[PDB]
Image (tube, coloured by chain):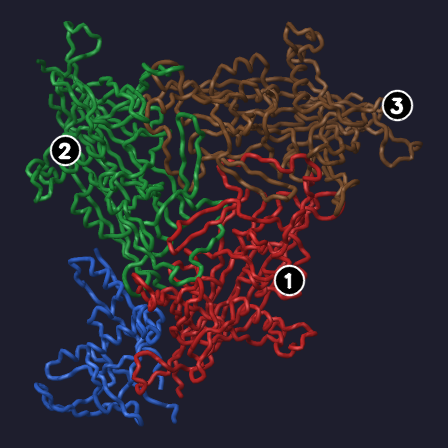
Chain colours: A red, B brown, C green, D blue
Amino acid sequence: PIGLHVEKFQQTYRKKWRFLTSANANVILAEAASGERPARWALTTGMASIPWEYLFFYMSPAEYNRMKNYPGTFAKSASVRIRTWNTRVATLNQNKFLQVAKGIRSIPFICSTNRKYTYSDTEPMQPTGFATLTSYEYRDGLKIAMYGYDNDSPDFAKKPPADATGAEIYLQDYLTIYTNDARATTGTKILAGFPPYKNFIEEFDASACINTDVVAMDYDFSYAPLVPQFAPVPNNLITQNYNASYPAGTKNEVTAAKTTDSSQATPPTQVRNAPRKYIQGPNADTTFFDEEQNYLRVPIEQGGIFEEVNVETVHDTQMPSINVGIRAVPKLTTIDETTQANSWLDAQGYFEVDCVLTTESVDPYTYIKGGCYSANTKSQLQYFANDGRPIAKVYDNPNVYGRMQMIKTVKP
Amino acid sequence: PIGLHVEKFQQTYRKKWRFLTSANANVILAEAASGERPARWALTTGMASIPWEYLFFYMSPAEYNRMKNYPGTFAKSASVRIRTWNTRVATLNQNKFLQVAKGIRSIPFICSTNRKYTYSDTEPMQPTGFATLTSYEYRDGLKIAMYGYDNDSPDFAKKPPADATGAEIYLQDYLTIYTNDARATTGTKILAGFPPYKNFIEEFDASACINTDVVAMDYDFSYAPLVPQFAPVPNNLITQNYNASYPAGTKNEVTAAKTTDSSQATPPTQVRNAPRKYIQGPNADTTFFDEEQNYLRVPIEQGGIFEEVNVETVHDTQMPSINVGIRAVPKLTTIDETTQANSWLDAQGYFEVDCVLTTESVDPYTYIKGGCYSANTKSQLQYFANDGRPIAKVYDNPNVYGRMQMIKTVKP
Amino acid sequence: PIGLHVEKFQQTYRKKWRFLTSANANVILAEAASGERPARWALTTGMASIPWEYLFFYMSPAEYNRMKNYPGTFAKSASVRIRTWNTRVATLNQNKFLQVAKGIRSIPFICSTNRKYTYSDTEPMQPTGFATLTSYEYRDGLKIAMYGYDNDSPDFAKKPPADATGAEIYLQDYLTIYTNDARATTGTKILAGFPPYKNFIEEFDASACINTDVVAMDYDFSYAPLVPQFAPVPNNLITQNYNASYPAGTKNEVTAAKTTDSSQATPPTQVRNAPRKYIQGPNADTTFFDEEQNYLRVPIEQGGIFEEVNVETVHDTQMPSINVGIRAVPKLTTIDETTQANSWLDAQGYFEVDCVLTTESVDPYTYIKGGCYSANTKSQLQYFANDGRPIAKVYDNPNVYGRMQMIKTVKP
Amino acid sequence: FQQTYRKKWRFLTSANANVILAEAASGERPARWALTTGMASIPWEYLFFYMSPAEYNRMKNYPGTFAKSASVRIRTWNTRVATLNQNKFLQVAKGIRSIPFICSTNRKYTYSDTEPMQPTGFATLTSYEYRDGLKIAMYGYDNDSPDFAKKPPADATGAEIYLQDYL
């Protein structure tokens, strides 16, 4: 027989961006202890982060607002291609080198985070501190640079849309590696210095790399729900059971959350039946999608966070990170008497990024009247905190045992 | 070396039945709310249920009583073949159509149940309500029709054994599809109508289908314990431990029960270490097998319900449903002025069912004296309720998220 | 890029032992009830246990003390080859038979344990009771026989090192099979006698077996941590999270302990997040390795006991047992009037054992300074009791449902 | 047990002028004239050149350790430098220390302010102190050091180290 009527819609979003990186110096910065954050030393790089894990990177505000009209939308794949151009920089015989880090965020023993620095006036290439800009605010400023303001905004003329002009956007969130600050540490100290992150990045002479793919990555999403599924017809209005238990075997079909403690004060634990809420139907909590976290604030893939009422397998996921930059060009001289450079040339990287996102949605017609209804096996759950604030996976924190953590969303 | 002595016994039970179906009209019936059961609309079909999931369908009271003498009996396979004959029915040029539903019980969005109707006196093919006969009572009446009464029964002459005569049995439990009754519903209503169940059944012209397999299904049981295993020699009489913990890995070897709520008032949960009791040995609770639930009241397969003390994998199971019937023949005429038929011809379906059940049992001789004893790794558990009432899987309830539910047995 | 610097070190330990077994008679002995231990009948064999599951069997005190200087040492494989020589024994035409039991400890329905007997003065081959020597003390005496005392020991001259001399060691821990003692049992009794353990052992005429491998076994360890890994740099000194939860899927990555009850008073249960402690790092509890349990008191493999903070799969493990011996030579005569022998000849088995153990360790250099540090994904946990006493798997207890149990270690 | 230690360094040399400097007599050292070169010494004969403090501290746990072999590969890049048509030349000395009649030593100079490429004297830095400063440049300080931020580890950053001990 013909069976169920389902309409499948595939959509593709392509963007082309041009980014300028700073080629900062590798300078150790002190960051003071603040609450749970310990005192630590921070070593800066010039390798700017490419926010390819977020939805604004691929699709504009118009495309996002239209996609919000297609329930059941899943991001199926993403792809990013990064090429490099001539590196803008007294001398004429400079040496310039291009640095690429792929998946350095996943490395368990390299504590790293993308940060924005403040720079010296005398040495514009030397970071002297940290700007208060968070990673979300960096992505938001980048989105406003990409797509402009609304026509009624009094600040409209300040940021012409790069999606219209094709102009370059200064890419100002660079990799930073952390180590202990044992100056005030009591008891036994860990004095291991820095990890040799040089051994985990690729470095080329970009003279021969011009207009060639320095980065080429493809990613298939395990579970990236962009719009919640159509709500099923609730069986509690039709059946007496609607609350029945059925025998699970030795298979797990309710996901669990694993909590680890690198302080080793507590052993790792795994807790099943975490607090979570439906994202469609009678008692839906669509706060995540109404606040539009997935567009700019949260990565596309949320594999371990969302759950369906089904026997499918769920597993933890993380997208690899991309950092592209240029090694700082030293200005070192004998009269400086230093073994390491204290002055640098104003180099600048020019990167061209082609990004493609493929998504797919379904319209199921389960009942004769009303509208689209899915099977109740397609009902989706999402982790929630005990304060009602949804939980999402984040990529802008240091990895915990090589894994990306899940935390409460912020926006009210 | 020769190892352990085990005797394997394979047995086969074959039955041939002849069934008459009614070919009822498709009439919407109202069923009032009663406790947990909401108000709902019921659409009837003429497709009678074939109880091939139950043990009486394959083996007679004598065979069942003898099988109860073979501990460790598992049903290994079942098979059903359904052929059709001439369809008995002023006019001479009628159109008759044969309807087959395979596995419509498993479909998540079709809320369906096999029900017995009461019919109009003027229109014998038009259901007008629901009989109080439950599915268990329907199967019990069918069993009494198949195998007769006991020779001392005062009602002996009323039901000649169809297993002896070869005569036809009126098969009177037909598929029914439920939808919301939002007439008294407060708040937002679901007005989706009925599912298009026409799109999920096969329909043929049975003129060319005569004496050909309209249905042919085979099923292999994952775990269908018909008689409990031989009790092992209890190691608490021989060893000091008898209560030792040993390290399970990341594998689950204790089954869990999953509870879902289509009302969405509660997220799905999975609970491990459900209340359960041994079915042989020192503290055995053989209430299930002493009350003989598996013969007539409970399906053959109980895959997720029973558990052994072993590392084997357990998974949830369900046998597909079979409904065979004939589309109602309308008696519609211009003077009726109706667009849909309100009068029908007394058609009748004639189906011949050949059913084969293969089972197997083992006699292990673990010790020299006494009798048969199995290895303690063959000890079996069964889910029980907190009131001592065993839990079994049932097929005569609407599916919950496409799964058959487990409930307490009824018989005291 | 070059990546992480890790040095891999493979080491091999070979020993050659010569063992003399007694060829005891098969005599039923009574063992009285004592606390949790019930009254039971014990049937003795002459098949001495080969302690190939323990580390002293393969590596000397010097090798053990040196290995303790290689963090991250895992035993990768073990291998044992057992050959037989002429069997020393009025008459000249004796019949001698060689008995081999492989994996009889794993058989669920044979309750067996290796025990030391006391023998009759008139019949040296007839056991008359049980010596108070436990299995640990047997292994300790065997180790002292193998490797001698310390040079300052006043008992130094009593035990010349067999590792130096090549001399034979009397191997005095023989297999014993237990059954019920229902003499004082109230209620229903289990009168099954003994299991036919004859059907589970190999027996040869060792006349043609001389200088040929009677046993040849290889074992690959799933998880046998001999020395704990290098502690990672703790991320709680560098990161704010250090306690973050991340979404496990439907996969289990925290191990669970399964408790069974052959008394059937309680159903089997599985408990996740058992009490356990880190064995390196900030809050390490290295009591197991400081007391040196793995050398002599505990088997090499502890697969289900130790756990890493990772997604790797853990599963329960057990090494097969080896018992080699000689059937007792009867001295039966007509004047005895007995149907079974009550006098025996002083036979003796001569076995030559070649044992090889391969292990491997890693030195990771994660940070620039300090020393070796591993990735925090290599951090190891071990089950602990609520009294702080570590939990290890033991092989010198009867199997519970065919599985080796885990218990608290003893040494303070 | 065989072990291997690999390092990758980037060095900047000064290209000093060939200037005769006077060094006064001091004790056993006679009065002598010193002619400078721009050829910086590569300290490939020392263990810090190949293995980090962590590797050294771990190796101290392996009695009987002998260094079996060493190998060094030196490549050159673009030479940074009014005019546009300069002539630049690369100088390599292999085993000039072994030559009996060439009295040579690797020294650190002090340079003129007006002519940064012209040595004007000798710095008090000895060869051991030069190697120690080079090691601190390569591997950083300890995390408790108050001077930690002054010298980022070149083994981590991959940055260039000014190589300032010339023939």
Q: Is residue B233 left or right of residue D57?
A: right
Image disc number at residue A265: none
Viewer can see residue A236: yes
**Mark 2 neighbour class, 10 Å CA radius: few under 14, some 14 to 19, many 20 or more:** many
The residue identified by callout 1 is A64
Residue found at x 26% / y 66%: D53
Rendering coords of residue B121 (x, y %):
84, 22
Q: Nearer the viewer, residue D82 or A340?
A: A340
Rendering coords of residue D158 (x, y %):
35, 71
Residues under numbered marks 2 and 3 in contact, where contact means CB atoms less than 8 Å apart: no
Q: Nearer the viewer, residue A271 or A142?
A: A271
Kindly give the residue lying farthest to the right in the view shown: B335
Quarter of the image for the N terminus of chain A: give it.
Answer: top right
**Mark 1 neighbour class, 10 Å CA radius: few under 14, some 14 to 19, many 20 or more:** some
Q: Are marks 3 and 1 on the same chain?
A: no
The residue identified by callout 2 is C18
Displayed quadrant of residue D127: bottom left
* Residue type, mark 2 in image: Arg
The residue identified by callout 3 is B90
Residues under numbered marks 2 and 1 in contact, where contact means CB atoms less than 8 Å apart: no
* Residue type, mark 3 in image: Ala
* Residue type, mark 1 in image: Tyr
Q: Is residue B265 left or right of residue C310?
A: right
Which secondary structure lies at badge 1? helix
Which secondary structure lies at badge 2? strand
Which secondary structure lies at badge 3? loop
